[PDB]
Structures are given as structure tokens and as C-alpha cells.
Image (spheres, grey):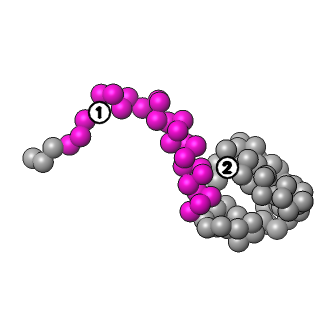
């Protein structure tokens, strides 16, 4: 999903993929992988997005985490895990 928000921000600016990659100082293919979600949004990328597009690094990272946590939540055996008690 983070890639969707990035592309939506770019559409509003009328900025193309190549112009985005150029400003981000990344290769075109890396930019595409980021926008399509084929490449996770790392801390360095979060920092770059904050400067180049806007908002804070955490905002971008949280979009990533929200998507990752949403996916992993149903794959974890939370049903059998228990809260630790004071020993
Ligand atoms: Mg690159």
C-alpha cells in the first residue's frame, strides 16, 4: 500500500517516475519496485521520501508496518500465545 500513497502524491505533483527516481537519487527500476510494492520501504527510503515528497520518515515507515502487520497478523498463531505472568 505504501507505494500507492507515494504514487498518489506524485500524481498530485504531476511528477513522473523518472523525475521521482532522480530526486530520490535512486535508479528507475528501484523507484518502480518501490511504487509497486515489490520492494519494502526501508528506513533510508523513508528518510529520502520525507525530504523529497514530504511528511515524516515515521509516517512512511508506519504505512509499511501497517501493511506488514496486517498481513502477518493472520499468519501468526496468536490463538495459542499467552501473556507472561510475573514469576
Ligand atoms: Mg537505487
Task: Give the magenta part as a residue range.
Answer: 58-84
Q: Please, is residue 65 above or below residue 59 in the view?
A: above
Q: Quadrant of the N terminus?
A: top right
- Mark pair 2, 1: CA separation: 30 Å
Seen from the viewer's position, the closer of residues 42 and 50 is: 50
Residue 45 occupies quadrant? bottom right
Q: Residues within 10 Å of mark 1 (few under 14, many from 20)?
A: few
Q: Please, is residue 17 above or below residue 33 in the view?
A: below
Horizontal side of 77 relative to 50 (left or right) equals left
At x 71%, y 42%, the residue is: 38
Q: Identify the disc placed on residue 21.
A: none
**How many labels, in total?**
2
Residue 11 occupies quadrant? bottom right
Read off the residue under disc 1: 81
Read off the residue under disc 2: 2
At x 54%, y 35%, the residue is: 71
**Can residue 24 be seen here?**
yes
In what element is the residue under mark 2? helix
Residue 28 screen position, x and y as percent: 85, 54
Q: Residues within 10 Å of mark 2 (few under 14, many from 20)?
A: many
Residue 14 occupies quadrant? bottom right
- Residue 76 within the magenta-colored segment of the rendering: yes
Q: Magenta segment, principal secondary structure?
A: helix
Residue 15 screen position, x and y as percent: 88, 60
Horizontal side of 70 relative to 39 (left or right) equals left
Amino acid at each position: 500500500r505504501p507505494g500507492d500513497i507515494i504514487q498518489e502524491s506524485l500524481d498530485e505533483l504531476n511528477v513522473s517516475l523518472r523525475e521521482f527516481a532522480r530526486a530520490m537519487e535512486i535508479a528507475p527500476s528501484t523507484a518502480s519496485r518501490l511504487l509497486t510494492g515489490k520492494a519494502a520501504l526501508t528506513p533510508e527510503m523513508a528518510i529520502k521520501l520525507s525530504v523529497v515528497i514530504g511528511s515524516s520518515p515515521q509516517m512512511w515507515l508506519n504505512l509499511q508496518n501497517a501493511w506488514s502487520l496486517a498481513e502477518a497478523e493472520k499468519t501468526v498463531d496468536v490463538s495459542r500465545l499467552r501473556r507472561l505472568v510475573t514469576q
